[PDB]
Image (cartoon, rainbow over all chains, first blue to last red):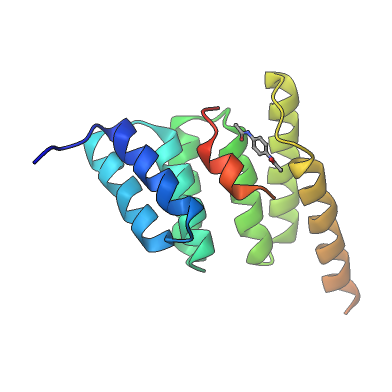
Length: 132
Length: 11
Ligand SMILES: *CC(=O)Nc1ccc(NC(=O)C*)cc1
C-alpha cells in the first residue's frame, strides 16, 4: 500500500474530526506525529479530540506539546483555555483565552467572535462558581 | 465555538 505524508494524515484526521469520529481522528493525528513530530498543529488538533472525548489531562498535555513547538499559536492557547474551563481552572482558562485574543490581534487574524465569546462565557461560569 | 473551523484552518 501507500504510507501517506504527515500532511495527508492531518487532512484525514481533520475529516474524521468534522464527523464526530473523535478517537479515530486522534489516532490519525498520532500517525501524523509518528511521521513528523515537529508540527504543532497535529498536537493542537488532537488535543481537541481528547477534549471531545472528556480526556482532559491528555488534552492539556497535547496543548503543552503544541505550545513548546509554536509559542505564538492562537489555536493552542484557545484550546488550552477551553480545556481548563471544563476542568474548572477558571483563572488559568481566562488568561489563556485572553492570550489567544492578544495573539490573534497581533497576528491580524480572524476567528469570528469566538474568542470574545469564549471569554464572556468563561467569566460567567467563574463568577457563578464563586457565588454558589 | 466553531471547533470545526478552528481545526481545519491552515493558520
Ligand atoms: C464561527 C467560526 O466560523 N469561527 C472561526 C474559527 C476559526 C477560523 N479560522 C482559523 O482558526 C485559522 C475562522 C472562523
